[PDB]
Every structure is written in C-alpha cells, then in structure tokens.
Image 1: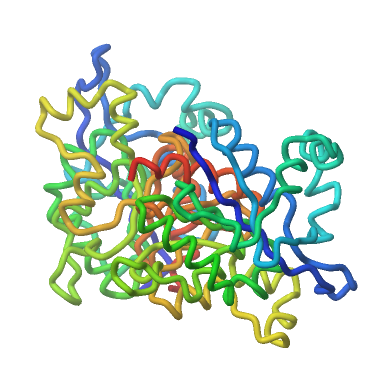
Image 2: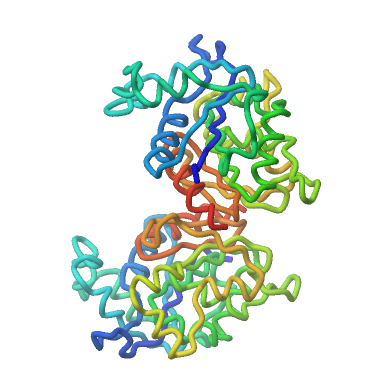
Length: 236
Length: 236
C-alpha cells in the first residue's frame, strides 16, 4: 500500500525583507521533509494555492543551503526537482490519496495560507480519514480557519502546538513589517483559536510537538524533526 | 518571595538494576540544574524526604559523569558538595523562601516522590505564590497527588508535560522491575491526573516543555534545559 504525503508550499513570492529581498518557500522546509518522507518509502506530491512558487531568497544563502541539500537543489535531475516540477494545484489533488498533510513554510505562508480554503479542506479531509496534519515554522498560519470536520470546531482548539516564535519575528526585525501588512503571527493564530502554544527555549532551536495526529515544528532547524514526528504519529 | 530555588532529591537509594547496582539521585540531574541556578544568581537549597540520599550508581559512569562535572563532583570543597552537605528535610524547609521548586530525578523517585506529601505541599505553596514548579526525568512522579491550591484539582490536570518515556523503560529492560515493584511510569502519572503527555522524538533527546509555570524535561540530557526553562518561566 503506497504511503503518500501531500507537501504544501506557500504560493507567495514577493519583496518582503527591508533589504529588498523576496520571501517565499524556505528551501529546507520543503527539502528536509521531502528527504525524510522519501527515505521512509513515502511518495511525495507538492502543492500550492496557485500551482506555482518561488524561493525565499534568504533561505538560498550558504548558511541555509549547503552540502548535499545544495547539490540536490542545483541538480535539475534530482528526485527533489523532478517532483517539484510536478507540483499540483488544489483542484488536481485527491485528498483520500494521502496519509499525511505537511505544511512547509517561509514567511510567504503568512500571506496565502490563512485564506487557502481549498488546502484547508484537503488537510481537514486527510485528518478526518485518520491521517496526520503537520506544519513547521509559519506553516501553522494555515490553521487559521482550519476546521475539524468531526467536531466542527477549529482543528487546533484545545491542542498543544508550537511554531515560529513572536520573539523570532522581533529579533529579525520583521515584526514592524508584519504589523504594517496586517499579518498575524503563529502565536496570534494559536491564541485566537484556543490552542495552547508551547515555545522552544530559543527561537532557532530544533523543536517540535506531537499532539495526537497534529504535529508542529518551530523553524527551518525543526523541519526534519517535524517530518519524522508526522511519520511516527501515523500510529496515533 | 526571595531569589532561591528548592532542589528536591530522591531519598531512595537501594539495589535496583539487574546487575545488582543501586539507583538514587542521577548526578547530573542535580548538578546541571544547580549550576544553571547559581549562574543566574539564585541561591539553592537541597532537600529530600529523609534529608539523606544516595547516587544512582549507573549515573556515576564516565559517560554520565565526566569533565568539569566529574571534577566538581570529586571536589569536597566544590560549591555543589558544600551545598549538598546542608541538605534539608521537608520540615526544615520554608516554602515562602523559594521562587522555583525543582524536582531532580533518577529511578529512585518512583519509590518516594509519589508519597512525599510534605514535598508536594511545599511545591503547591511555591506554585500558589506565583512561583515555578519544574521536574526532569522521573521527577514528574512528584505530581502524583500534587494539588493546585487555587482549584483543589490535580496541579497537572489540563496541563501539557513531558518526562521519562515508557519506551525508555522498555529499552533499558527496567519495565519488568517497575511491574514487580508496582511502580507507575511518568506517562502513567500524567494519564491518571488528566495531563497531556507530549513525547520527545527519541527517549534520550534533550526535550523539555514550559506550560505556564509548570516546567518538565525528559531525561538527564534534558536537565540543563529544564533548569533554564524554570528560570525563564518565572515571568509567566
């Protein structure tokens, strides 16, 4: 029986940082989970609201993209790039095909995930079928409006999750940008929908939580752990 | 409400392992937190049910005790040993003198912490006064019967915590000992008192949780992080 994962990417790719650089998909938040899932025999399909995406430019720097990751990223024939080329649109997705819905991130997600009704519907179905819903970094932004079809209440209500920290936004100086663009942080989303937010000791720590079949991670350093937890949570 | 920490130690020190070795206080679970609190300007008082304790023999191994830790451990004039020498009994303790109650562990805690009514009352008072209650490894055994003065309900009810894993007991082959000795695991205690147990990816990982002013860690590798968390939590 083919084990499949639907890996969502932000469809937002535009100027964001004060240096004029664009945000979008944080490379390793898509690549590490991809590698982790593939390693365990899972098939992975990518998807975005528009079927298109762009890379967060800061995630392209050597500090965040190097070694084997950089090699796979540059190799047009890598399993990673070939699968990205087949990225789907929500309409082209058959929710019942997946056991795991994983929301990769980058700040771009703050723009499209909250309003991604179709992806939320898919995630909701996958969860309703007993599958796992995972999100890393700003990925939990998609929990804004994500309803549990069984209870009809927010999927994260009464759940414990983690995700990008408010303090991280402040340290990066993007806090003023989020406010100016009327964007809500992960902690804002958690508070709004009655979820219990549990923070990492430090904003850049590899930190993740598994609450039943709801798995969350804090940042790029947590992408691998988040993917690992999503696989383990299949027994929940 | 002075700047002091009450560091609880298990008073149990008897043969426990299959190799005939005894359990007791896991050295680094007392030392690492001790160092962290002292570094941040806190005064530390040690305490145990009987005012006496013994070291877990397996925690004396080089893999668990080495470097500076091993030096401070062997130096009779070390601030650590000098403070350990002044270890108190619950009756000699004044709960209003502490901001943080920290329960160090080692398997021995499974024998005395659940019944340590006097230590639980102290922990309850410290928490009621707005202080922090923390526990690492098997330390959460201290939560068995621990009541929240504000509501009369179990202090951990409705709270998210972590602690030593059931799988870790199995891997160590000590599960048969707990069964024979009618002991409850940390996960058993969380389940019994309505807490949500959040597990680490691996049983030996440095993993900890801060849920308001209730702080928990999984194992020896998590002792430092648990102490760090208890300090940062004083603002929650």
